[PDB]
Image 1 (cartoon, rainbow, N blue to C red):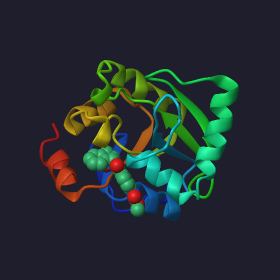
Image 2: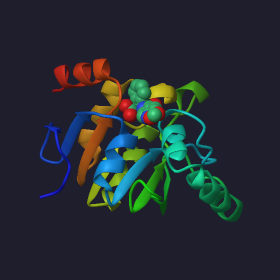
Image 3: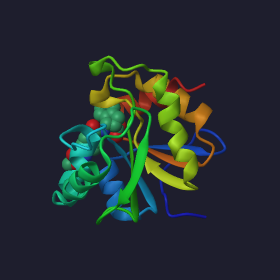
Image 4: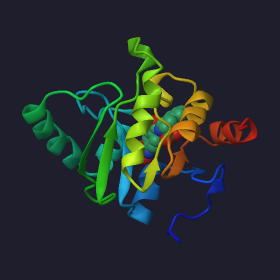
Length: 167
Ligand SMILES: COC(=O)Nc1ccc(C(=O)N[C@@H]2c3ccccc3C[C@@H]2C(=O)O)cc1
């Protein structure tokens, strides 16, 4: 049993809710919140910008030190950093950004990072300002992630479309 509430069950291991991931993280304090990161960990907008704003820019400060030491992530890759006031840990995962021309096949590699964590609160990778089709992202999630994932979808209209079209 865990503290996630109000989710619709899509599969054995994938759950979905119309929710602001910032507000959900603040209430649940999950072990892992996933950030929709880019390779530079520049958290300017979308989910990343919202998560970073909620940390009062501490996420960005930590991320800048990470990049200065380690260099950029790979598209499809991830790193574990602090969850600050939102979670124990933040798993920064880089899905391909279609608005930069990155290969959508890398979306499966991106979701594979979730399998290193037993339970996660996450957005749909490569959705929103990353330009992929969220219905496709949900399909890849369900077909790739085997650990327990709680998906937060900010837009109610999109949430309803994701549920109604789910196979
Ligand atoms: C004040 O609080 C906040 O700013 N919160 C906040 C701000 C932005 C986003 C976001 O860009 N989300 C992504 C988004 C947007 C449109 C379509 C698909 C998706 C996938 C992501 C999701 O559905 O979560 C999420 C939360």
